[PDB]
Image: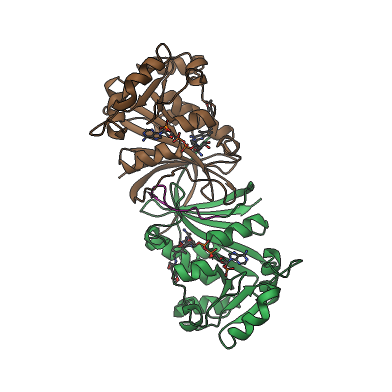
Chain colours: A green, B brown
């Protein structure tokens, strides 16, 4: 009942985007994470040390394919997010697909307690969205006037983000091809709200020991079954997986 | 730089053991764990809910190949370990390889605070080892007389297990082909002591949310690079990976 996986194909620059195609229509929330073999999401507090050239390449590709990159403010601070960068060819590909040259960043915050000073606001070609609650949306909008488009993403509860609503507000703005890059709290909520369509997971060929948190945190205990759409690899033993919710 | 992995081979019952062969000589500490896509080691407190027929098959195979199955007492209690079971054919294969019919269980405990009552002691064809410290080995041996062979596994510090010493004591008893099945504390120590030779990791196609711990816990922060030896899959989207320390 077991099948050996082997490299059967070198992916061309044209085929790789195809493997990570978004659906033709409808919203699609894709997550891109990286974790060690022993499930650690961080090395020395952040994820980058696990990411080699292969993962950076995939990471940048998923950004290139996304209409919008949604990230928790925690990751934004910790990973030092600034504006999404797109190279000339990336911009060309994006135009060819009917997309803006650079995907927007969307920072998720229940508190809305974002400072005007952040690099997500400062070092950015594209002004970012701030996805927050109905309760704080107005004060946040005022505080962040000129810096970010503040969008209330509450459903029934004005004090919380409803993640389905969040996805919908993005789509409503024509940002239906969503990529989230974390963090584990945000991902946890997406998973709990059952709005995660796809998880692209780089499995870095490291064990990192017990300190690191997982790529999902929170009190949530779910068991969402996913289908393995693909596994890619590179010469360094990384697995670039793509799982789609069943 | 990216290669697509695909199933290229259906593994026969003869080839599968070959993929998980131990080295011809020397000690080899292999770990077998299972984790969800989001790095969770447990569902509802234990690992079994993530394990389908494929993982059980691999799990049983690794047991069949091992001279000894080393587990923390935590896992022993929580997963309700009793004696290793071997079917007739499993025993035959084991004999053919020069191995005893059933691998021993080795329970690791720094405290040595094991009760005579446990199923590891009671429902077992083979009496298990208790790998513990020099400091408690004697009282533990007395307490567990007739139930378990108690082995002191301290190196410099009589109050602790030295995991290299643990591996050595096993080999010393002709149990050089070691399988550890956990838990995360034990695995954490193996990883910290740098004695983990190989990690066989089932990646179950689930996200489980933030509650679960990882397959490694502890204060440890390492970055042990591993080489991806193989990835198998089944029809249900599980990845059966084998990584070998570089
Ligand atoms: N290995 C990987 O792939 C990966 C990927 C990303 C991040 N990381 C790492 O994980 C760490 C950060 O963890 P984190 O959990 O704090 O990241 P995070 O989820 O990005 O940040 C948490 C914050 O974002 C907001 N948030 C998240 N979900 C929300 C929701 N459903 N509704 C409203 N607000 C929401 C909240 O902000 P407010 O407090 O303002 O309400 C929350 O406090 C960093 O160390 C980073 O390196 C790893
Ligand atoms: N997903 C998976 O593949 C997988 C695999 C195994 C277990 N699990 C799960 O993980 C959980 C158990 O976690 P756990 O960390 O408590 O398991 P554990 O490592 O098996 O148990 C911990 C105990 O074993 C002893 N121990 C471990 N390492 C030691 C060392 N280097 N030296 C001396 N003693 C050592 C200690 O016993 P003393 O206190 O007596 O000193 C320690 O308290 C369960 O929920 C189980 O389901 C999951
Ligand atoms: C400044 O913005 C950036 C932030 C980060 N943060 C760390 C980082 C690294 C690898 C990653 N790899 C995957 N698979 N998924 C992630 N979620 C991820 C993250 C979160 C990494 C960047 O380069 C890869 C980057 O530049 C665009
Ligand atoms: C009674 O002993 C047993 C204990 C367990 N415990 C849970 C369990 C399940 C799947 C697993 N799968 C892998 N890849 N690695 C593990 N470490 C593992 C464990 C730890 C599972 C058993 O059946 C699979 C079993 O019977 C032999």
Residue found farthest to the top? B146
> In the image, residue A108 lies at what x, y percent?
59, 70
Residue drawn at (44%, 68%) of the image: A79
Residue A81, compared with residue B154, is above or below; it is below
> In the image, residue A11 lies at what x, y percent?
46, 59
Residue drawn at (62%, 80%) of the image: A140
- Magenta range: A203-217
> In the image, residue A131 lies at what x, y percent?
63, 73
Residue found farthest to the right? A156
| Main secondary structure found in the magenta portion | loop
Q: Is A18 one of the magenta-colored residues?
A: no
Q: Pick whichever, A137 or B115, lies toward us.
A: B115
Q: Pick whichever, A3 or A204, lies toward us.
A: A204
Residue A148, compared with residue B123, is above or below; it is below
Residue drawn at (24%, 32%) of the image: B155
Whether residue B15 sits left or right of residue B22 in the image: it is: right
Quadrant, the N terminus of chain A: top right
Residue drawn at (54%, 27%) of the image: B80
């Amino acid at each position: 009942p077991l099948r050996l996986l082997s490299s059967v194909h070198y992916l061309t620059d044209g085929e790789l985007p195809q493997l990570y195609d978004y659906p033709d229509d409808g919203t699609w929330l894709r997550a891109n994470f990286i974790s060690s073999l022993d499930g650690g999401a961080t090395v020395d507090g952040t994820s980058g040390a696990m990411a080699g050239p292969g993962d950076r390449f995939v990471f940048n590709l998923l950004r290139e394919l996304a209409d919008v990159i949604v990230v928790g403010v925690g990751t934004v601070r910790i990973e030092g997010y600034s504006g999404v960068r797109m190279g000339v060819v990336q911009r060309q590909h994006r135009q060819a697909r009917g997309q803006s040259e650079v995907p927007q960043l969307a920072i998720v915050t229940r508190s809305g307690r974002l400072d005007r000073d952040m690099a997500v606001f400062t070092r950015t070609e594209m002004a970012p969205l701030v996805l927050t609650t109905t309760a704080v949306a107005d004060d946040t909008r005022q505080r962040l006037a000129g810096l970010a488009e503040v969008i209330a993403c509450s459903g029934d509860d004005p004090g919380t983000v409803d993640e389905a609503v969040l996805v919908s507000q993005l789509a409503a703005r024509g940002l239906r091809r969503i990529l989230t890059e974390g963090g584990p709290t945000l991902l946890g909520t997406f998973v709990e709200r059952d709005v995660l369509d796809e998880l692209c997971l780089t499995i870095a060929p490291y064990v990192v020991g017990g300190l690191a948190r997982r790529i999902v945190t929170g009190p949530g205990q779910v068991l969402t079954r996913m289908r393995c759409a693909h596994v890619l690899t590179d010469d360094s033993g990384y697995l670039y997986t793509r799982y789609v919710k069943t």
